[PDB]
Image (tube, rainbow over all chains, first blue to last red):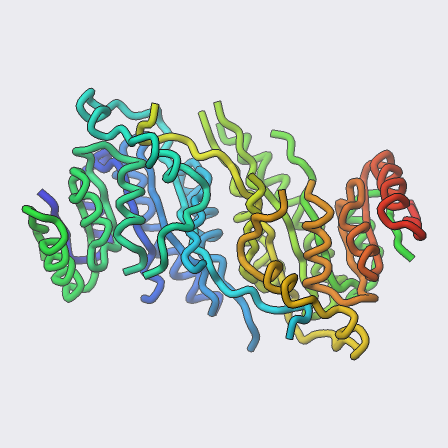
Length: 232
Length: 233
C-alpha cells in the first residue's frame, strides 16, 4: 500500500513510529528578507527533526534544492543553510550530488544558474541489513551503477521540483525493494511514483489537497496496476 | 609592486586600510582533524571568519571574495565536513552577499555505495554598497575574447585538470580589471599572486610560513619573468 497523507508535514510525521522509514527523497516547498528566510529555515528544521526520528539507522534524508536567486543581484544559499542546519540535528553529512539541470565580455558578468544540489544526510547508527532477496532484487547492473554513483548528473534535463527519472535514480541507490520511501513535501507525488515504480512502499505528505488529488491521479496513470491512497 | 607579507592573516589584514582591495582569490588552509571533532571543526570556522571579516572591510564596494574549497572527507565510519556550506552561511552573517558558486570538477553494485569526491566549490561572496567604475582603458584591456568569456562564465568548470595557475588566472580575469589589487590571505606558494601579476593586476599576499613565502618569491620570479615578489614581514 502506498499512501499520501494530506496535512501538515511536522504534525503528520510526528504521528509516525520512530525507525519506520528507510529513505526520504524530497524538495523543500520554497515557492511557499533575512527574517522570512530564517523563519522558513526554522520550519524546515522541524520537519527534518521528525525525519531524523522516523529514519531507521543508516537511512538517509535526500534533499534536492536549488539556490534562490531572488536593490541588487544576490542568491540565498538555501542548500548551504539546509546542510548546516541538518548537522545540528544529528545528521552525518555525506557528499552531495550536483544536478546539472540546465546544460559585454567584460569582468563582473553574472553566471546564470545551471545547477541544483542533491543534499545527502545520513542518520548514524550502524549500517543496514537487507534480506537476501532484497539484495538480489536491488543490485544495480554495472552499467547503471557507474552512471548513478558519480558526483555530477548532467543527463537529466530540467522539467514538479524534479523529473521522475531523478527520483527513480535516488530510490534505486539508497533503498531496497520493499523499503518505505517518504516525501514530506510530496506535491504531485513524483517521489511516491518513483518508489512504487520500483517496488518500494510509498509514503507521503502534502499540504494542498488539490495537489494530493493530482498526485493520486498522476500516480494511477504512471504506476501500472497500483493506486495511491489519499488520507485527508 | 607585488607584495607578500609574512605573518598571521588576521593581524596583517587588520593593518590594511579599508576599501583598498578589489578581488580576493584564496583557498582556506588545510585543516587537521563524540562531538569534539565537530567542535574542532567549528573552531577552525571561527578562525576563518576572522580573516573573512577583515576581507569584508578592505574590499571595495562591489568587490568580491572568492574562496575555492573542497569539503573535508574522512571515512573508515564515513563522514564529510560541509566546509563550503559552512563558509557560505558564516559569510552571510558578516555582511557578504552570496552569489552562485562555480563548481570545479577536478576529477558489489548494491544500494548505499559511497560517492567519491570529484569537485571543489568556488565560493563567491560580494560586498554590496555600490562599485568602482573602471576607466575606459581598464575596461578595454580587460575585455575577454568571446571564446574565453563563454568558457569562463559558466557554472561548471571541467577543463582544468592548492589550485592550478590556470584556475587562478580565470578568476583574476573575470572579477578584476587591469591595475586592480588582488589579495590572497593564504598565499602559499603564491599561485594567486602569480596569476594577478601575470595579467596586469597588483598582487598582494599573506603567508604564515616564512618558508613558503620564500618559495613563492622564487616561483614568482620564474612564472612572472621580468618582475619580482617583494616579501615583507
